[PDB]
Image (cartoon, rainbow, N blue to C red; front, side, top):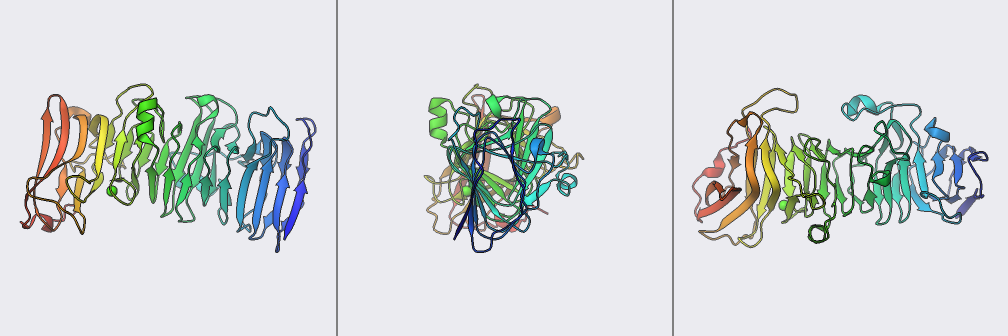
Length: 421
Ligand SMILES: [Ca+2]
């Protein structure tokens, strides 16, 4: 049944509550109520529900200042993080993850991992409405196999502002899909304070918040991220969307080779596309790049390895990319070596499509086409094994479009060439 650890007390920085007795859950769910200042430093083993009701902004999983953390690798259950607002006026109500004196390098993820807090890699974690999940100062990482957040929750990153403070949440190792519906943004929306997501594993993470500011960017190493915020509302009300705006230099999304970005919402930051772009979410949709808050151009940064997949049901229903900015091709690969290979467009009619001769599909619309070093480039096209196509790259009235036109319902062999060789 249930064990309850009620550790709450109206305490201060000078009277921390510390609980460190090992827990073997057995057949019991646990419910733990923490004080504002709490060191929850118990080794936990079991496969039951562990619910952590956090009484303030100094409840640590581990010790003060994130100096150490207990073993949770034998915890295989569900960790649920809730607020507990009995003590009012706190900066936030949630859990501070520890770093164990270790620093994370977002540029060398593989080399950072084996010394990063990886205790929550055999369980699931759910961050509930009103709860915050934060880290301390410095540049820190945590590996969480499966994280879902509810609307009204906050992935904060560092508990305090600073250019030297950065928090990277390495999510997805379970291989399962998850939903980040709560906010992802640093304290005070401070632009210099970094909070980042690093996506690994085979599954897809869906991001739906409309007021994010992912200052440490999303780095997609494996699987997919869908930006599924309410873009129509974000346009009208001038909201940040799923990413927010990082400016004209730093990408908000790095899609590495083999991984994918997609969705029905929008990025207000540069997408650096080494990998795949799949508009919609396992189906037809429109993905937008646009900054509704500050009105600046947002470019799609294309690479020699870029691939863009367009599913097409009809002239009325097909995948679209809209860029309120330029298609900006960099002839530099993931390894910094030059290549003259250009992005591939995959034209993919559905199994029950109603395409007709003369249908013109505007797959990509942008303000312009640009390039590192002003080197001219065109998309390579992977045609399907049906119909006959003309692809038209059109610059007109100071705007750009990539159009696929159906010339015949008969097949003319255009799909026999495997472009990616
Ligand atoms: Ca699609």
